[PDB]
Image 1 (tube, protein in one colour):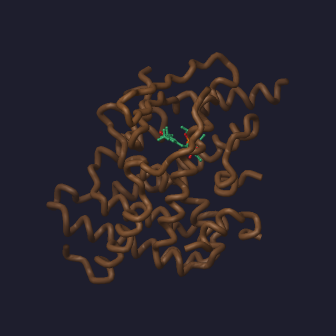
Image 2 (spheres, protein in one colour):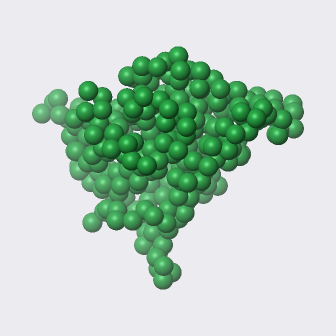
Image 3 (spheres, protein in one colour):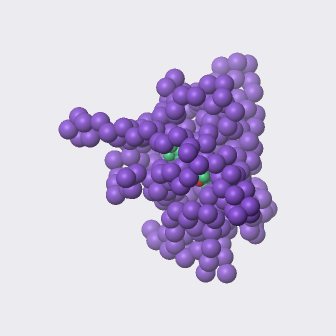
Length: 290
Ligand SMILES: CCOP(=O)(OCC)C(=Cc1cc(C(C)(C)C)c(O)c(C(C)(C)C)c1)P(=O)(OCC)OCC
């Protein structure tokens, strides 16, 4: 090990939260939906760009051994480019509920004021959701293996690595991180002091730095040097790149939502779709429960 006692216990708590709130087999993801003027033309034309490189087919395995596969329609210029968004809204909403439950287990997060707990969740939800997706992603077949469900990227590796979120998943997977390293990335992402609407900048910054040092010292003392000499800094680089991709994808959601509303109420709150506690009643209730 080689970490202080505060540090070994800090990981213990994160790992615990991860264990209690991450459904790696997706056993409990049920009841989800499946497919069955000049100003506005530029809006639709930008949504096509927003959606075209994020297309997956869907595989769904049945208890009996049957397989249902779904290939999405090719872009014919109409509403058909939205066929998977209701299913994704349910998958992402299921994921965020787990992220919220993740944060509340953590003493340092729980000790923060409700309004700051909200702001931290609004800024980190996509990021922590995508870090969790990374651990079920298979880079050899381009597939997120989510228990009975599978999402495969449709062939069209050099054109894929153009979309920043897809390059991220490949780069991150290549690093071969430990469970403990993934969960530490989550904390560092969660306790970001310069999220919109955070009040206790000083406190959150102190907590983040405390988590980064634990990740830095975890790597020093659990990896053969100087092979992984810069793994910590690589991870920090990808956290920063992940903060940027979050913003881009949040703006994508809003453009799509503008012309084809589909976001769940929890998503509406998380991403600013229309008092910080009074404008986020679902989050507040989700945070005030046990
Ligand atoms: C705020 C961001 O929205 P969002 O959370 O939820 C939308 C319903 C988000 C969800 C998402 C993104 C990806 C990419 C980007 C890695 C391809 C996925 O592979 C997956 C699955 C479920 C297939 C694992 C889900 P979006 O980035 O990608 C849609 C595939 O949606 C933004 C428009």
